[PDB]
Amino acid sequence: NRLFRKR
Amino acid sequence: LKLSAKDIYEKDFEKTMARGYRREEVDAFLDDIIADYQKMADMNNEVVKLSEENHKLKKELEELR
Amino acid sequence: DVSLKLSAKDIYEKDFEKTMARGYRREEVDAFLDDIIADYQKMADMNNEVVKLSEENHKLKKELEEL
Figure 1 (cartoon, rainbow over the protein chains, first blue to last red):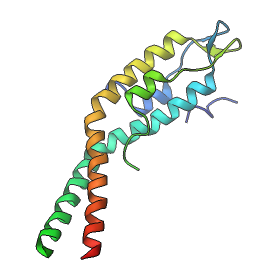
Figure 2: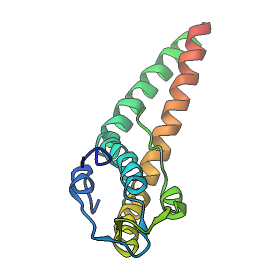
Figure 3: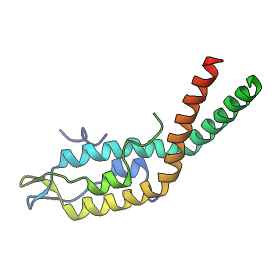
């Protein structure tokens, strides 16, 4: 899941 | 298929201040596509299971007239 | 669920809000979605079949239920 992949 | 669910997760694009697309809008949409690719991978087997069930249910029917 | 939520058409039509902060280059996103479109086109027929078998089996279970 790439929406949650930073910060 | 040219891509896998994994390739889409892994993919990174170049950032820009010059009217680039909203990152969270892009990543949310690609997460829906990731799910769809997972389903694409299982689909042939799901078609096979469904046609076997299709056949079983049709035999039962004809036997019950 | 086993059928796709999106189609080739949905991905072609999808229009992303622009930002003047740190955003993705439109060229790269657009080019990547093109490859994705090609894969949705290759699976569209098998996906139509999955929907149809699901709908048919549901109706057949309903028909058996009544007997």
